[PDB]
Amino acid sequence: GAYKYIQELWRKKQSDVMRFLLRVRCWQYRQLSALHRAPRPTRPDKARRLGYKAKQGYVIYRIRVRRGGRKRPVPKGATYGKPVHHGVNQLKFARSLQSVAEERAGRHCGALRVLNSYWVGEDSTYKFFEVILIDPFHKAIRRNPDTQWITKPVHKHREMRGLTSAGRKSRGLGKGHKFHHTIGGSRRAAWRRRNTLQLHRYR
Amino acid sequence: SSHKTFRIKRFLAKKQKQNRPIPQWIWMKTGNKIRYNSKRRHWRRTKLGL
Amino acid sequence: KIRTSPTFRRPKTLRLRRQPKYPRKSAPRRNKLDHYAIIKFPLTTESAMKKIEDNNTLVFIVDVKANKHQIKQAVKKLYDIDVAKVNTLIRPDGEKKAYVRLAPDYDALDVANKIGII
Amino acid sequence: APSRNGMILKPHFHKDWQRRVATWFNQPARKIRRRKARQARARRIAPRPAAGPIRPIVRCPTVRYHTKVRAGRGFSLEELRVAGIHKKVARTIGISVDPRRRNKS
Amino acid sequence: TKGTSSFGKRRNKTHTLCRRCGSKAYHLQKSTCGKCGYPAKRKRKYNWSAKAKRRNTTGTGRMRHLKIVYRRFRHGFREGTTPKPK
Amino acid sequence: AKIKARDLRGKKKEELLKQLDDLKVELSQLRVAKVTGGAASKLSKIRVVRKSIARVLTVINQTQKENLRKFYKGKKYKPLDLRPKKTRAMRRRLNKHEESLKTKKQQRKERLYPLRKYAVKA
RNA sequence: CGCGACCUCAGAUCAGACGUGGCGACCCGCUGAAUUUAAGCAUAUUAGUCAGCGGAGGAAAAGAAACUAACCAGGAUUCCCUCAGUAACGGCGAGUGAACAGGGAAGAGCCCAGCGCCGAAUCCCCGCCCCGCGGCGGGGCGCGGGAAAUGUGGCGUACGG
């Protein structure tokens, strides 16, 4: 099939053919609004890998995120605390820029459900991502047993709670000795269980 | 003020109909502890807010 | 086909009318301000009677929502009489009082006896 | 201020522990709820065993324990292959299966 | 003159009745309720005042449409049925 | 005459209205009797009239509604008044049919590997 | 020029839907102090805590190993006992501080993309017929409309197929 070629071709983002397309797209995406619907996926292969299926109910928004770190929003620097906290400039956000993208596309279209996102191009000031949305009230989505899990109310705003693939990575969870500080549900689940006196009845 | 709004005038209407003493026959009821109206507002002492 | 003006304006597109496949609400809400809800009761104060014999008017406590137009057609329909003009004010207690001046061919003093106030 | 002679104690009570004290007064109620749910389950699957599927015999790792034997999670696929049991049928007759296990011995 | 004499010039209200929370805290010049933030879609509530929360929560009012849900719940929100006639 | 709702439901529509305004009229002149210092007996009657007007209005509203939801019985779209109102959260759940949908693959497992009923000896 | 495709992109009080706000004890994602302790204090500590912001559910989150181990080996997640105030961190000061194994509670596993085969074998909607019709669904009939080859469905997923 052709999807293997398209996949392995997108693994050559330095080649001349790819460097041309990326700079051409990144030019065109820079002329549109920060958040606008795309008619079809620009990366059909990546979309299918992430769960997109070409059928009524799947929506794709391409949104733009300003690159760079996060500076502490305090007036003129003034962090009236101890010197350990005077940092204003080289601070980094705890969540990826892709996860910020999934959030902004999900907050705008509250009726839809964020599924996944992927990288489609960047420059010195912008990263462009294409988020895959699903309309959980379309009968093509509602009547399909394979995808009707997204319709359940527990998956309202997966991106706001950090449950998408891009959002999960910032939570630092996984199996093994590298991820001890999130044993339990999450980083707060571990902290509670470890800072709770279990005062038994008989001690 | 002589220049009022309909919101204000209707509001002052309520606070005026509430300023009456309790009727005589209520403390003839069985489980009645009320002796008199404890929310009587006098226009010169309590100034109704606003 | 040429552009005489240097500006581009959004062309006028056809826009249809609502053709709903079902009424949003089952049945129209019945009017809760009919003629009987407008006129609550007339007044029997010493100034109200004084207003009847002299100026040939009737004094009513109408609902606070009614207009002079609704009040005029209410008394015209409840008591089968003709009205010259209606003056309304909102009492300090809250309800709306309406001075209804009858047309000269009707004597308000007898009209008050049909409705009972005297 | 340490007195004459004692231990150097380090009580981990410098956080706001009083806000996160878990008391166990529901313990007897939990033991009741567990038992009732355990009996309700046994009645639902009445002829089948109450404990559940059979577990395999399993050694313990970590030389402190390798002289003992546990009940594993499930039978390995080659144990089922030699026993002549299809791996998608064994759960239907109460045989715990986990495909992760290997057999070195 | 900062005391008694200056209290005489007080004849301009800054606040009026908010039409969302009913409190007299609708700042006129700022057009914002200092009690519920009326023009803001979301209600103004802060955890640093627990006492101000419980003054205005879901059990303080009438619950004219919620106390019916609590009643309809204990029958499974049945609908379209009537008790068998006599 | 103590107006009972058992007695109203068999009547035709526009004669119920003819009885409605009749009580409306009687309530008005009873209100007039309240300000002209009327007898105590008539003053106690306005409560009877008020609740009798509510009764005839209730019958009118009820009979009109059930004529509507009988007219919208077999139709696909119906007004929001006639749709079952139960806790918006569960107006959004999947149907009694959708949640029962199994994939052709998942159905093939049930036919091939159904959960058996067994028992182990002592 | 005309006409028609298609691709992008607009406008509708277009037909039918959906989102917003509240509560917030419990839960998830961020953000995030300083009192305080160190007999001073700046790193540390307080503390990933309070406050702040967002989003849920009847539970949430997690979850079927890019695991633990070094054994004669265990075998998703969560919870309890223990490991253990331990290994480790730390002006190595004050203080901070897990995990594996082991015993229990419970126990359940699975699906895609891809790779390929099948004549798109797939789905939505309108009209008609039947069945029920307060969870608008089932069957049938439509040279009825649309989606879809820029990939729908069935088979099939690392335990191999």
Image (cartoon, rainbow, N blue to C red):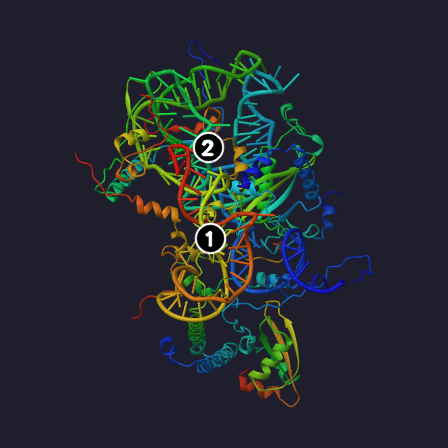
User: Image height check: is B1 above or below D30?
Assistant: below
Q: Under tag 1, what secondary structure? A: helix
Q: Quadrant of residue G103?
A: top left
Chain letter belonging to callout 2: A
| Residue F101 on image: x %, y % | 39, 52
Q: Nearer the viewer, residue A103 or E26?
A: A103
Determine whether G27 is above or below G68 in the image: below
Marks 1 and 2: which is nearer the front? Answer: 1
Q: CB atoms at circles 1 and 2 under 8 Å apart?
A: no
Q: For marks 1 and 2, give the CA distance.
A: 34 Å
The quadrant of the image that shows the N terminus of chain C is bottom right
Report if residue F89 is visible in the image: no
> Split into 4 quadrants, where in the image is the C terminus of chain C?
bottom right
Label 2 sits on residue: A189
Side of C4 relative to D72 (left or right): right
At label 2, the amino acid type is Ala
Q: What residue do we see at 72% from left, 32% from top? A: A76
- Residue where numbered disc 1 is placed: A142
Q: Residue furthest bottom?
A: C105
